[PDB]
Length: 188
RNA sequence: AGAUCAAUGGUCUGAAGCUACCAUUUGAGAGAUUAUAACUGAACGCCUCUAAGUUAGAAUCUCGCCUUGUCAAGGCGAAAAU
Image 1 (tube, rainbow, N blue to C red):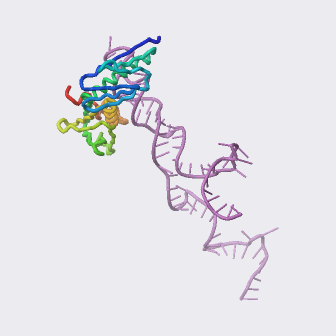
Image 2 (spheres, helix red, strand yellow):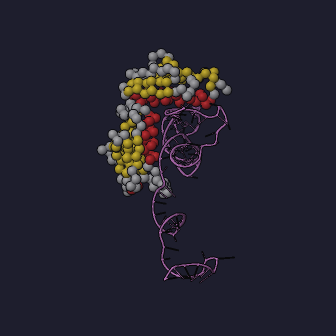
Image 3 (cartoon, rainbow, N blue to C red):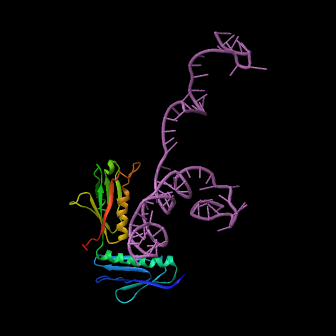
């Protein structure tokens, strides 16, 4: 069944603008600007008023209609990124071996050492627009921060999956660095 | 003394050439991705690696390096003398 019309709207708080057209959005706020392309979906996106963006679909099937809220949530994430940003805190857990985490290449690469005592050095590059920092106060804590949630979470996932155990049971060899918290930069 | 014959008379040494893991030398990179693990995220106001979109990804696959390249829209250039 092809529903005649189905739409959703996103409302923008004060201080941020979107200026959408041709299915590419250009959200801008205090923390810069994020541009996202949504041309893989054949919906109609337009400005209705001053701070409302409407995403609409004519004659869509279940699978196409499922994407309206997806796009709206993506735009909401852009708003959050430009207002308060994104910050992922990850904790290192080990039984015996301290996981030594450092930054090199102009603070653009994360190096993991001593993970389970292996002499190999694990190198993870950081996506553009994302930064990293070790906590000097809270030990064993690494923070990856940025505007774009997609890239921030991709960097966090890269770091988390970089540390994996092999040939030993993960039910009790729990060593590794895990994403413990997902929050915003500005205290909410 | 010099040699010849015995279908290579026989024994010892034997260069040269050929030749032995029986001697010596040389053998390696990317790209898209599978299984899989994940990101964001609906459907299904919650969840979810999946539906749209994203990551990492291999003795596999494609290419690179390497061999041929008298190739019928007679495969295609440069340049010399005619």
